[PDB]
Amino acid sequence: HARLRALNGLLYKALTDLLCTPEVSQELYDLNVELSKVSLTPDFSACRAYWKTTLSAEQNAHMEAVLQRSAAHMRHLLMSQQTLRNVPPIVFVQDKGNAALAELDQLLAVADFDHEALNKQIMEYKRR
Amino acid sequence: PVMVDEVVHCLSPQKGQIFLDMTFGSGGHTKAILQKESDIVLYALDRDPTAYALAEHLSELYPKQIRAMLGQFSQAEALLMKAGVQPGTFDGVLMDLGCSSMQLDTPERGFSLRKDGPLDMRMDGGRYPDMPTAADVVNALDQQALASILRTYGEEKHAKKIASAIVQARSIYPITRTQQLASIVAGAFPPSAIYTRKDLLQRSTHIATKTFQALRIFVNNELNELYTGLKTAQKFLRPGGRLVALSFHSLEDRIVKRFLLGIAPLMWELIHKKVLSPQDQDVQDNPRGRSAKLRAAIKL
Amino acid sequence: TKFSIYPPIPGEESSLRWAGKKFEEIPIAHIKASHNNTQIQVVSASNEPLAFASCGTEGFRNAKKGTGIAAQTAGIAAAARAKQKGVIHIRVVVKGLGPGRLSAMHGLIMGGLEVISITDNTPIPHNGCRPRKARKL
Amino acid sequence: KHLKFIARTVMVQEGNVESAYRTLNRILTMDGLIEDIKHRRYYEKPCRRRQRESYERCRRIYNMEMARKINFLMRKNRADPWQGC
RNA sequence: AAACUCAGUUGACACAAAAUAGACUACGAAAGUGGCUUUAACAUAUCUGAACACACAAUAGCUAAGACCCAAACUGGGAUUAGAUACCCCACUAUGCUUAGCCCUAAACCUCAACAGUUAAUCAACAAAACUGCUCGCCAGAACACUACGAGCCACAGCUUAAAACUCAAA
Ligand SMILES: Nc1ncnc2c1ncn2[C@@H]1O[C@H](CSCC[C@H](N)C(=O)O)[C@@H](O)[C@H]1O
Ligand SMILES: [K+]
Ligand SMILES: [Mg+2]
Ligand SMILES: [Mg+2]
Ligand SMILES: [Mg+2]
Ligand SMILES: [Mg+2]
Ligand SMILES: [Mg+2]
Ligand SMILES: [Mg+2]
Ligand SMILES: [Mg+2]
Ligand SMILES: [Mg+2]
Ligand SMILES: [Mg+2]
Ligand SMILES: [Mg+2]
């Protein structure tokens, strides 16, 4: 739906601007979190921000924990900036899609080489 | 001819130019075009054999300047290939949609619910006897099929109710008359709801008008055949030729708009950016042509 | 001694030099990072324009202008033009909070020019013209 | 009308331009300039501003009280000295 | 997309608006009042006291004359729509400002009347713990009804006061 797409783009831009600043918290800015996309629920119940995860598992867990802690504060900041009148709760979802592409790149470097349907009923009724 | 002045001005008939009229019908637009330009070459195609005979008779006025042809949009390409113009090179194409004034005024054709007629509602006038009639359509299609057809073609919100009423009525007695079907459609709603629905003109209209429109479209397959006709007109039209399409309902207008806008580089140049509409006084004079929207383009 | 983030005071006996020049002599690089664009202009110490670049000038159009890559490309182009005019060290002053606010700088660094001081001059009306009403969607 | 390159100016240290930019951004955040810049993009109506300020004050007070309570009760979190009783 | 051929650095430049302080909780009868200076100035120590007068009363609005940054109903485009409106983008007006009058409405809400007193044996519930003394105003099922009529008003699609008949066993 067009409105959902526009809202997704606006929220993605706003969140990207938010995370490029120490505004939310110094630790979150130091984490230098990136986003791949932002998707809204069809019923506007929640806003899922898909953040890219690094290779380090412990660093990934730390970043996810900080994002979960600061999601409510970021929602309040978005509502304060009036980027959206009613902002649904923000859920930070890990994105491991790029890891699969990276591993494929690593391994490939060593890989070797309507009307007609009812017309039947109409025909049958005419014949019958 | 609805918006005859606009069509004449936009097409700009000129000497030695080739023009096609994919829907002759009454031929009022064709007659006006031949009136303005006495040296124009015109081919007029229609589905109604009555309209084909009318065009043949009117060919007495213009022996060779107008050439009549009988067939659908799908048959249009084959018939024009038989004529001998595969490139076409037509300097213009005119596509008037909807139901003919002669077809609707005649109760025998069954297009009018106001005057009782057989539930034919078939633009074909005996060329294809095996073609199903509206009575066959209503007596054949199931509840879900009829509801889907009504919802998609007549834009009827209450397609389920009308379909169920029609199914019950056909189960009781066969449905063969236009007034019978109109009474069945009215019975699905309270009697006060016979004229509750008001058109965009804010005048009371029969509640069975949408059902009749949907049934006519499904009988004649107007959407897909209009798509094929537009494609054939694009294929046959001369480069720089002028295509003028007249619509009477939202579905065909949407189809024409999407085809013109390609919804890839555009293959049309809109002569008029916004859709042209008849004068309000002209709308009052011709209530039937109120919903006639004009879309004009040049082949690119 | 030790490093000081505070810029050296004009008209003061500051021993710091850059290519033999004083801080008041180092050319300036203005970066206006608007919400959908990034315009970069290099001027001398005497406000003499030397290089100008922007996402539109680089060929990016519409939303492509409001991207960090476009800002980096504009920075690289402006840095190349300034280097062709003899610019090495620059004081960067940036206004606005556009997406390219940092990215342009990176491009301006990739062109070979050295940034000696990062300055913010974002227009902040203490309270001036009333801003537009909040968008509703 | 003020002198240039004094306000919101950070000198880069040995070329760590990224670090200098992060320091300047932290300074702007601490001084609240970023908040003002982003909140002045659109006009916040006075009633909305008052509601937001009251909510922020209440949230800050509640967070401080909760943190103080947690810190005060953290002393009890030692190992159990009376295990089995 | 439309439209501007303007955009950027620097300089000059308001009758508009009043970052941070303000995480303060002050002033005023309330409405309200958060840039700076100066002048004038914040009633009554004995309480209460207006359909019964005097004087106020945010925003919106009217009348007249100005001011033009920005904002902005309305309108005109741009997209979008089958088409049209709304939302989004652009331009722009009444209007927000000043002067001089009007209008006298707000969820004008701490939704908890003014004054005095008590913390003793708690209190339907929820809200802001429970009461006492005293005074003024107001209420007596819902709906009809921020209505009709009458009257008053600088008000003329207005405000204030404010019913009845029919109907319901609820609200
Ligand atoms: N797919 C199709 N192919 C050929 N003729 C068609 C057609 N669909 C409709 N027609 C015919 O074209 C007309 C459509 S409406 C009538 C318009 C006509 N120009 C007039 O003024 O009379 C009808 O006469 C109908 O019979
Ligand atoms: K101020
Ligand atoms: Mg008194
Ligand atoms: Mg009083
Ligand atoms: Mg007032
Ligand atoms: Mg006023
Ligand atoms: Mg404006
Ligand atoms: Mg108030
Ligand atoms: Mg009182
Ligand atoms: Mg009222
Ligand atoms: Mg009244
Ligand atoms: Mg009266």
Image: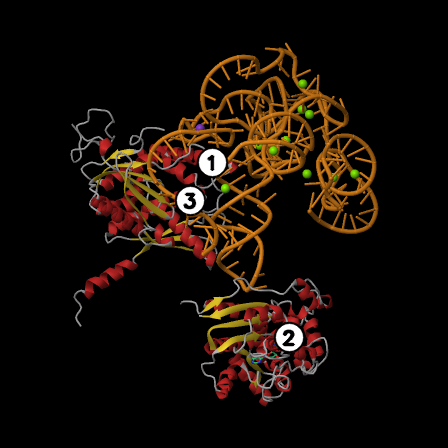
Left or right side of E106 for B229? left
User: Which of C101 and B256 lies nearest the eye of the viewer?
Assistant: B256
Which secondary structure, mark 1?
A: loop
Same subunit, labels 3 and 1: the answer reads no
Q: Which residue does the numbered mark 1 point to in the structure image?
A: C129
Callout 2 secondary element: helix
Residue B168 in sight from this viewpoint: yes
Where is residue B292? Give x, y as percent: 61, 68
Residue type indicated by callout 3: Leu
Find the distance from the CA under tag 2 to the CA under tag 3. Answer: 52 Å
Query: Can you see residue B189?
Result: no
Residue B212, disc: 2
Label 1 environment density (alpha carbons within 10 Å; few <14, some 14–19, many ≥20): few
Up the image or down, E140 lies above or below C57; here it is above
Q: Nearer the viewer, residue C30 or E18?
A: C30
Indicate the amino acid at tag 1.
Cys
